[PDB]
Image (cartoon, rainbow, N blue to C red; front, side, top):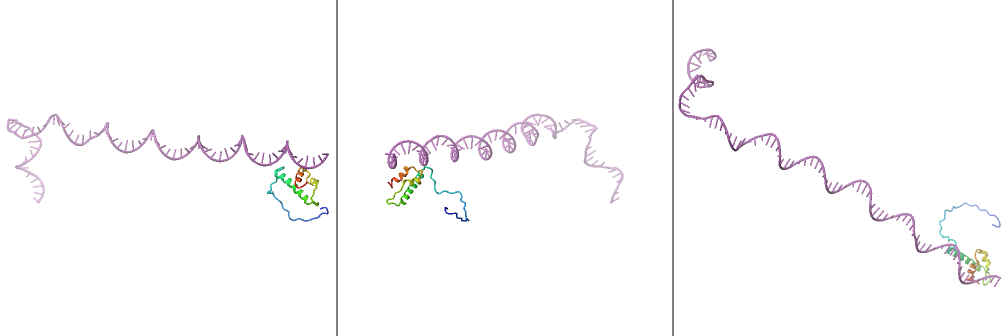
Length: 85
DNA sequence: CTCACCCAATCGCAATCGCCTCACCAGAGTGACTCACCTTCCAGTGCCTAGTGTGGGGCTGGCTGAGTAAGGATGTCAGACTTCT
């Protein structure tokens, strides 16, 4: 860590074979894929509103632009259009 | 001037179809076996040649009669004699 080194011994190590997947990975730019994208952004926006101390709760746009910098700001505006002004 | 919203365009994903390929099923042909029919051979039975019994239909000798006749072989006696008792 930042403060120093720490040492443990280990005695047990597992080898994991070939995985049998139980969850389907979406494809690039698929409906489910981009749905998760806008949902991840909406959840982050709600949790930034919960963390806000001023009443009424207010956030800044460039916090979201620091978190999601590949997003066009039209999509972030779209998420903030409902629930904020 | 800057920001936000709306519209348009492009890309990606999903669904449907699309025509070609593969697989399965069915039918036909091929090969062998079995069965049936025909043909041939053999065997048996039923009549033609050969070898024959038994007989028809002729055919010719034999038959007392009494007379004329011979030697005739055959024999029935008849006697004389030699053997046995």
